Length: 139
Length: 139
Length: 139
Ligand SMILES: O=C(N[C@H](CO)[C@H](O)c1ccc([N+](=O)[O-])cc1)C(Br)Br
Ligand SMILES: O=C(N[C@H](CO)[C@H](O)c1ccc([N+](=O)[O-])cc1)C(Br)Br
Ligand SMILES: O=C(N[C@H](CO)[C@H](O)c1ccc([N+](=O)[O-])cc1)C(Br)Br
Image (cartoon, rainbow over all chains, first blue to last red; front, top):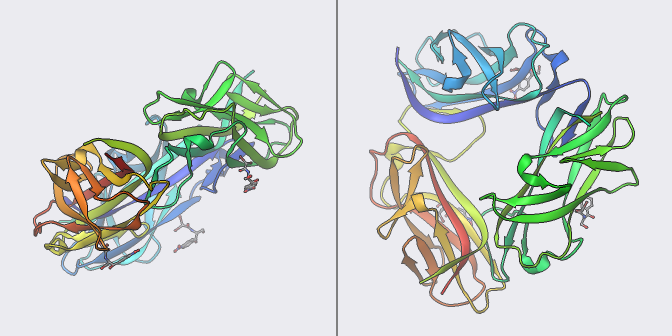
């Protein structure tokens, strides 16, 4: 399997807090750790492919966001993980291969990829968490 | 005194220039050094607390933004300071403790924190200055 | 010649991709390498000067964006260059001097600076490219 970077980058951010939550400045995605229940939605990621009639659309996670077939948002200090599941909102079939999430069939797919909490993680340490995904194609 | 990070981060930015000022790209907060008079407003910082009925709301400045009971925006190269005063627009009572600005009474406060130039600093070197404040609670 | 930093910074970004292009997240400026033809427009840069009746308006490129009288966007890893020409949309006369693009006559100029591909570069490696320009004056 080989991923070819060819596209833009989408960044999913989430600030985890305690019950007493202090929002400073402009609105951003924030949740209390108590809200990090199994399958809790974190946010959608739009995907729009062009010129891929003969390639399999793919998204590659930053090195710090995957390890051992698993994906996760990572804290600013690179220490804490928030495991997630990545799933298209439609019925399309995809595969995971070492940090790469690719579509099973060729074509210029457009769609929404949902990012969901994988397993209850209500003990997550408060902090700023990020998941970075780069567009490209797999073969 | 102890601060518990629990909330989002607000960033106050200011570009200081000379009288001949060249604005490139999108509008941003910029002032000539001549405008850095005592009590000159730099910008507001919104604060919205939730779930803090039994905690004292607090904002903690980045390590590089405070020293010796004083707050300041810091240049990109970490060298130059622009001393400021931090004050809520309403009549609420707050206290400063080693980089932490906390509310005297418990409660889920919502309000505006003003950032003002502390003492005339019309000699400030031109550059990009930042003040970073993180939400949480104090005890 | 001497440039005095005095103003804000404008950042021109461009993501280069292959024909199969996967856009992830919010819209950003992206082009296939095949679109990097000679004189292809990359994007405009607004300039608004104030208080410069007796100074020559100038823009200085980041150190990593110029070398030997030539300007270029640079990849995230600092390795790959995309040579460009910088030109005002109006009929004003400007000069280039070691990374500095300055106006020939004094005055508080307001205008648009166009960034164009300099020579066909359809072999550019896919990646994220940036050109940073800071406002100030020259003498
Ligand atoms: O964000 C997700 N789900 C939500 C909240 O349930 C929602 O269903 C939704 C769907 C689609 C879009 N969109 O296309 O912009 C926004 C919000 C998940 Br996908 Br993680
Ligand atoms: O910015 C401040 N003051 C100004 C300019 O005087 C102003 O009064 C104002 C008040 C409130 C808001 N707001 O709630 O968004 C914006 C501008 C200071 Br506070 Br530093
Ligand atoms: O972007 C440029 N040119 C385009 C596309 O041709 C266009 O002419 C244009 C002109 C002016 C503005 N503007 O003032 O915001 C936007 C787009 C070039 Br300049 Br590189």
